[PDB]
Image (cartoon, coloured by chain):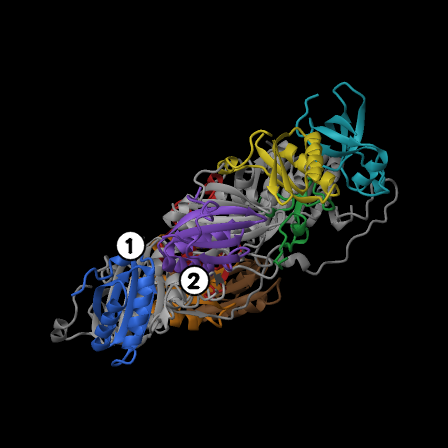
Chain colours: A cyan, D red, E orange, F brown, I blue, K purple, L yellow, N green
Amino acid sequence: MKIMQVEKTLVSTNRIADMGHKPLLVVWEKPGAPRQVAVDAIGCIPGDWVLCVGSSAAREAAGSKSYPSDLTIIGIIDQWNG
Amino acid sequence: GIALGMIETRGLVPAIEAADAMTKAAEVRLVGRQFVGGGYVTVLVRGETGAVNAAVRAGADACERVGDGLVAAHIIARVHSEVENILPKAPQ
Amino acid sequence: GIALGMIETRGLVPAIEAADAMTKAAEVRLVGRQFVGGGYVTVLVRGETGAVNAAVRAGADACERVGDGLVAAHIIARVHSEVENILPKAPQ
Amino acid sequence: GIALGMIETRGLVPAIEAADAMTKAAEVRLVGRQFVGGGYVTVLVRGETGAVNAAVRAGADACERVGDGLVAAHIIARVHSEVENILPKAPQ
Amino acid sequence: GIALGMIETRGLVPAIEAADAMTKAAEVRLVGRQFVGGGYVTVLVRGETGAVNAAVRAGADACERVGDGLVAAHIIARVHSEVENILPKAPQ
Amino acid sequence: GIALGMIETRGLVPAIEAADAMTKAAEVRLVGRQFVGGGYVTVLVRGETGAVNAAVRAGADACERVGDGLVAAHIIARVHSEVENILPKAPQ
Amino acid sequence: GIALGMIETRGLVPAIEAADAMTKAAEVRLVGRQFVGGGYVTVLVRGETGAVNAAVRAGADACERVGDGLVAAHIIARVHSEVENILPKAPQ
Amino acid sequence: GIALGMIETRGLVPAIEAADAMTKAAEVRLVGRQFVGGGYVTVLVRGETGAVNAAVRAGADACERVGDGLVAAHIIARVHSEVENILPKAPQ
Amino acid sequence: GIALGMIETRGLVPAIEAADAMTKAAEVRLVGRQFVGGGYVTVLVRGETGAVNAAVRAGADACERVGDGLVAAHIIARVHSEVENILPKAPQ
Amino acid sequence: GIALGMIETRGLVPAIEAADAMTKAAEVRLVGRQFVGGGYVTVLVRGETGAVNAAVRAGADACERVGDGLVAAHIIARVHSEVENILPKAPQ
Amino acid sequence: GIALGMIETRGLVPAIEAADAMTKAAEVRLVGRQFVGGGYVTVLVRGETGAVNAAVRAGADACERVGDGLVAAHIIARVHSEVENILPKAPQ
Amino acid sequence: GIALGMIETRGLVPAIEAADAMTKAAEVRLVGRQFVGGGYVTVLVRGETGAVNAAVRAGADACERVGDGLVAAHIIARVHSEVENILPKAPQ
Amino acid sequence: RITGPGMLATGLITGTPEFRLVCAPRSDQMDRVSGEGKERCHITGDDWSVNKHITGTAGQWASGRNPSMRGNARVVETSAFANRNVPKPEKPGSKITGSSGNDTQGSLITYSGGARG
Amino acid sequence: RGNARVVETSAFANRNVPKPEKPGSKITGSSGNDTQGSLITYSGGARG
């Protein structure tokens, strides 16, 4: 897993149906870092330091063995300052 | 952001879950929570149509199994001018 | 903390019992009690995540067999700033 | 005494009967009546734990058959300080 | 008067019929009409003990077939002094 | 005209229909509309006795199948003065 | 009030119960308890006739299943002056 | 303590056993022993409600088979103020 | 010797016999004879437990066939202080 | 207060839960925890009678499900002075 | 007195109840409580023969259904000088 | 932190495994290991509520299959001050 | 019958001259008064409980004092919970194609007109 | 050798001691609410 900070939300109205209704968040390891997008399965606010799982697991955390996700937020770390 | 998203639930706990989800999912502004009566709580968010869509969807899924659950999740993209007088302009 | 813990119960006795269990169990503060209509009463606590989790579990057990019961117990670890507008700050 | 007893009934008539009974049966003070919503009324008394217990059992019995009857009867011997903010101080 | 007579009905129309019948039947002062919640209405009368008895009988007989009917008809001859605080003094 | 005509309906639409009907049928004045709670709305008309009878009947007939329907259609030719405190004077 | 309600019981425990019940039940003042011998104990209350009726029914009901129970429950609505001489004037 | 527990026995031996039991079992004060007549003897304890309840249970059990036995065990948690005048305040 | 021994008999002749028997049989001191009423007379001895036990057996078998006989023969080994207030200290 | 409440459990986790519950539920002071041997742990609380009652009930409800459970819940309301030597005054 | 009464119980709660009962019943001194091992607790009282019999019987009757119960209740009237070396002098 | 987490296991090997796991999972202090008797061993840790929760769950999962296993795993987020006196402060 | 302290414990005392789940299943029980007034657990000892012999305070003592009549009035609940099973019109489906994030396996979202969204 | 009543009291003996029905969680929200693990309890005996 990786520790990254949610920066903002991401809206893609033309997403695949398989993606479901699940929310998507723009997450970076640090500010000024490569930005990745994660399905949020926890309910995470911007500025949160969160735990993001890798690919097969991401799908299952995101909701199914056959879900289209390669990065899902699985927990918010209670105290972390990066 | 002139679009409207509303989620209605049986209870306030599902509504707070819905609102949280919505506002977290997309850039929408919660503009109201209304106690309809009878246990119906409606939470309304306003934003761009895509944003509102996303928000409502995440919210409906989130609140569905919380408490007594979702009654309705509705998105109205262009809201008529008349309807705006009945819609809350800021949360209370 | 910014975690929110919410219990909905049918009637106020279950809710007062839930709040009591919750508050005694963990370091959470009761920020409100709400009458939703239809007899749904929601008690809302706030605190850090571990505290809130503990409290919500305790409250739920306590209130389940009291009165007409528990409708919902829910934990939201981080609450969006927008949701905070519709959330009570002090019991009152 | 600082214990709390509560009777929740469906309707006010059952509750008033319950309150009367509770105060007559033992050394308790009525501190509140609340209309929860949806026809639930809660009558709350404070006193010593044993007194409170006696009073509550008596109120329960008196009110069970009046009107639509009893929903809940509960006693809390020590109330957390937070819970006291949501609890009524004197009858209104 | 010391005595209290309370009639609880489902809906206001039965309650008005009951109040009228009570007030006409005997010398009782109507001291409150309470919309409890859920459609329950309680009409409360105060008077001497014989008067309250007559009044409740009359009121119950009146309201029973009107509307959704009578939930409870209750007479309390001396209400404990504590209970007097939760009771209305003049109808509002 | 001191007579009271009262129609109670489940929901406001049936009640507005009832009121309209009553007032069109007879020389009665609408003195009030009340939300009892639980979905009951009572619409109240005052007038001379024959007028009130005609009106209430018209109103009932009109509202019987509108919405969720009628609960009570009742007439009281002279209400006791005590009751008049609980009855609305002007519609508002 | 000058009515007299009297209850006779077999034994003192039933009589204390009766006295408590009567005094709680309605607006009557306890005037005495007399031991008659052979285990009969008589408790007397004074008040308005309606009050006395209520109180006495209540008292009889209370003592009947307590101990050896009730021997007699009687109400004299106006007591002759000569009789007042043999009546206890303040309790014990 | 406000509460009153009373044991009635046929004979003094049963009463002494009951009293000893009551007094040993819980924190109560024997406030009276009375010879009613006819061989009924009443022993009376005052204490807080839980104490009184324990004491009466104990005394009753004890005296049930001592002598001619128990007639009555009764507990009144708060007695009306008037009933106090007829109650013994110190054993003699 | 702090134990108590008690014999209750129907009538005084059997009681004097019992007291005499008891005192003669063992090292007990007679502390009282009481007329309970109804014909019950209780004679009471104090002594050490073995003595009291001997003396009560003696008294009982002595008075059983004298007169109307024995109602109770009972031994309490440690007597609570409260009870000592209701017990005769010295005979006569 | 001098009443004693004791909960005996199999194991220390259940007992600590019991102590915590007991101390939170009522105004009782923990006086000891003892390891009996064989895995029995007894936790003892002192307080006024009603407090003790509440605390013990609460503690048992709390510990029944934790671990291997509760062996016993007991209240000795007035505790003889001799026993105080075996009982632990302040916990270790 | 040198008589010894001993009650063995499984666990401390039964033993404490036994001690209380014994001490309350007769003039015996608790001279010891021992934790034997395996969950057994022995409570030992010394006093005079009759007193010890009374006390042990009382104690047994008390602890039998409390907790895991009574293993053994025994009385030894005079204990040999050698067995006094193994017997606890003071309840420490 | 002030939360307490405890694991009681049957045997020491399971407990050492649990303690290791707990201390490893989160930032918690092992404040004690106690041998209760009969083979129960209890390992107790302190820290923040979240830390304690993580630790206890981890430890539990670890020891369940080690040895004779887990008896109990418990978490208390707020410990009453009174309980602190029976809890170890450092591991000895 | 010499009653007294020596009639106690028959069969449990030796050395004499002559010899020579505490708490009820939860599912089964619903307490009249909950909380600290619960009776699920068997608390032995000098507790606040009242037996068969004891009379007073609660059962007919409270339920008799004040006269009452109840009526079998028409009870119809109008609430969100009561309407949980209200009859509903047939659920809207979506025939749209193109990437619309057309999830059909989740909750019902509706758009203007009642359209599935 | 005498015959004596053995009621072994021990952690091992009590392994099978009759127990109350185990706690369940009706809580919702992300709380790491695992159900398949060993029982963990919180105050009041609630599953945690």
What residue is shown with label 2?
M50
Query: Which x, y percent locates residue M71?
Result: 48, 70
Q: Amino acid at mark 2?
A: Val
Q: Chain of mark 1?
A: I
Camera-side residue of M54 and F24: M54
| Label 1: few (<14), some (14–19) or many (≥20) C-alpha neighbours in 10 Å | few
Q: Name the side, left or right, on which M96 lies relative to E56.
A: right
Camera-side residue of F52 and K51: K51
What residue is shown with label 1?
I81
In front of the other: label 2 or label 1? 1
Query: Which x, y percent locates residue M64?
Result: 39, 68
Q: Amino acid at mark 1?
A: Ser
**Marks 2/1 same chain:** no
Could you say whether the residue bearing mark 1 is in a helix, strand or loop? helix
Camera-side residue of N16 and M7: M7
The image quadrant where one finds the N terminus of chain F is bottom left
